[PDB]
Image (cartoon, rainbow, N blue to C red; front, side, top):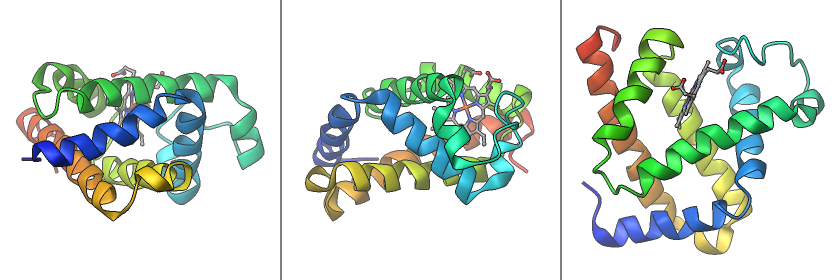
Length: 153
Ligand code: HEM
């Protein structure tokens, strides 16, 4: 359970991300695909991309980064009361997209890295710890839905 002070740190940096949702979404997906190439293989939509320059040039990838970050921002702004938002996301990611929880840990690392690069003054260690707690809570709740459905592993 995050404290109110922890949530304020999370949402303070997130309000900065929202100034350039698409730039952040590109940086995060590119970091994820470069750091963990098994993740790119889950996207029939993107698996033709073979270089970072091709990734940066793809408008469709930039569009999907906005989709992703808009869904994450709506979950963070619920401050833990996010059951309605996680149901469809866990369902699609477990049963249609076939995304292991571990890959959610990988995109969490990529989000934290990109927030640290772009917002260092609002992403000191206190805010890094709070964002890690928020993303851990996200993963915990999704993993419980995966387990229900027979996909936790
Ligand atoms: C912060 C974590 C994530 C969020 C908020 C998120 C959100 C979304 C949303 C909103 C969609 C479109 C609606 C839907 O299908 O449910 C989507 C699609 C998808 N996501 Fe995620 N996602 C996350 C992580 C991941 C990861 C880590 C992977 C793969 C390693 C992944 C793979 C996919 C795939 C394959 C699609 C379908 C893309 C397409 O062909 O249109 N997602 N995601």
